[PDB]
Structure formats: structure tokens, C-alpha cells
Length: 168
Length: 168
Image (cartoon, rainbow over all chains, first blue to last red; front, top):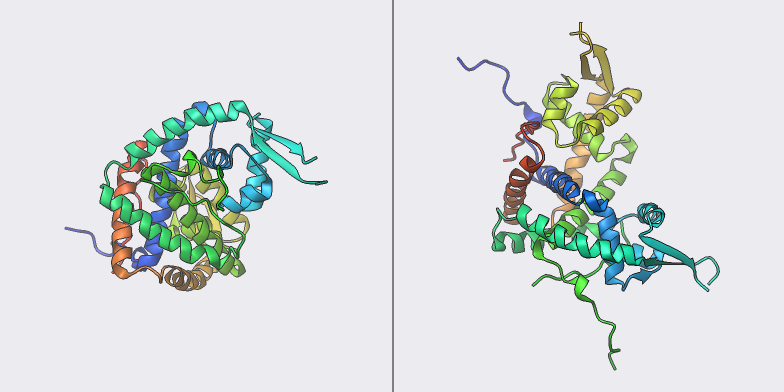
């Protein structure tokens, strides 16, 4: 009755650490796809939202090198997103009055867009994560933080001072 | 002595579910940056490795629609990566002998590249995750799986039957 020789092969049994990478990538993709669709009326990707948010923590104005130090993304990636945000009227770039340094500032449109986006985004993440308990959330953040702290210095050698976000 | 009015602002305190998204994105980025550098002599991104791995679970040969059902990525993304892998001699596309259906098969070069990549990749993930205990790993996979199972159906409605990877 069950067919022979068609069950899973050895490549479907993983080391646990490889399965954890697959789990992390699948949760990142599934949450981002759903969040991005909810935020589409504001035209925000997760990375544009992350840059608006970092610049709000910096008081709406900073420099490319300070923004890059605070955020996990590669500098070329942060510059590309900032340039797109500038075309969209979210960031204003001005020459420092230091030759060649640029200051980046959020426009009032960007700050009002962030007001709206933060409120929707908090509702989205809350409803997405409602099926795990407070205890499971607190443990997940602790374990992910241990992984971040052990793995970030394998390639980021004093280049990042990531924003020390808190929760209550 | 401490300066006034320069401490963090309200945007540095997040809802826990938003902080969990930041934690997931930071761990994904930090692990991928380190892994990609170790695998660079095989010219494999994490997504090319994931497609080679899914096709090994399928016995080295499948169709674009079956591959897409098994993997989390968007179909356009899977097609773009498969097309790049075809240019690189990793995938062979042949017309089905069904008009317009394509069969995709790993080349023997791709299977030998996967032999090498899987062994390096298992060592990389093991050393990256050595700072969390077996118990913390098992709980992390359980909690991430609950998040995946609750969030994937918000946008994938019977479109995916993700490979049921196991560990021991």
C-alpha cells in the first residue's frame, strides 16, 4: 500500500544549526511579505522604515557615517536607500558649511510618514506575534541577542555601535 | 557632570514585537555576511545554496513550479536565481518532451559543489551558534516555527508546501 523508495532523502535531515538558519530566513521572509503589503500606502520597505526610525532616534538629522554605525546594514546599502529616500522627498542632503561632508535630515513629510507608519507597524507586529506568549517572546529576544552578539564581530570589527533599543 | 538633554529619546524604546523584528533582521544579516565570505570560493549566495539544497532533496531534478512550492522565496526570485545558476552551469533546463513546461536538473558540477558547500556550511553554522546551548537552540527552533506557521498563511494561501526538514 505505501509506495516504496519515495520517502525523504538524507538531505531533508539537517544539523540543528542549519535548520535554525532556515527557520530564521523563513520567518524573516514571511513577516516581511505581510508587513510590506500593510505599509504599501506609505511606500515603505522594511529598510526605508528602519532608516527613518534610526534617523528619528538621532533627532531627525545626522551624517551618513553616524547613521551607518548605528544600523546593521552595509554602508553601500544604506547610501543607496538614502539616495532613493532623497528622490522621494523624505531626506534632505546638505553640504556641511567640512568640505565633502554631507548632513542628512528628515523632511517634515518623512516625520509625518513615520508617525503614521510606526502606529500601523506596531499593530502589524503585535498581531503577527500574538500566537507566542510573553515568556516565549522575552526568551526569543534573549537568544537572538546572544546570536547577534557572537556573530556580528566575526565581520564587523568596531564598525558598528548598534542603537541600544529597549522594550518594557 | 553627565550632560543634560542628550539621552535616548522615545523612539529607542520599542514594543517587544517590533524589537523581535529588529533582532531577527540583525541576526539574519550578521550570520549571512559571515557565511557568504566563507563560501565565496564556491561562488554561492545563501539563496543559490538554498536552491541547490532544495533540488538535492528533490533528487536533483524537478520543475520550476514544484521547486517554488517547496521553498519560501517568491517565484520571480526563484526564477531569477535559477536563470543565474543556469548561466553558471549549475542547472540544466530542458523542454519537457507538455509544450511550454521546463524541467530543471542539477549538473554533476552543481552536485559536487553542493558536496563541498554542505560540509563547509555545517561547520560555519555550528561555530556561529556555539554560544547558545542545545536547549536554547531547540526552544529557538520551536518558537520560530510557531511564528512561521502563524505568519506564512497571512500571504501564502496554499501556494507553499515547504520542505519538512528534520534534525536529530
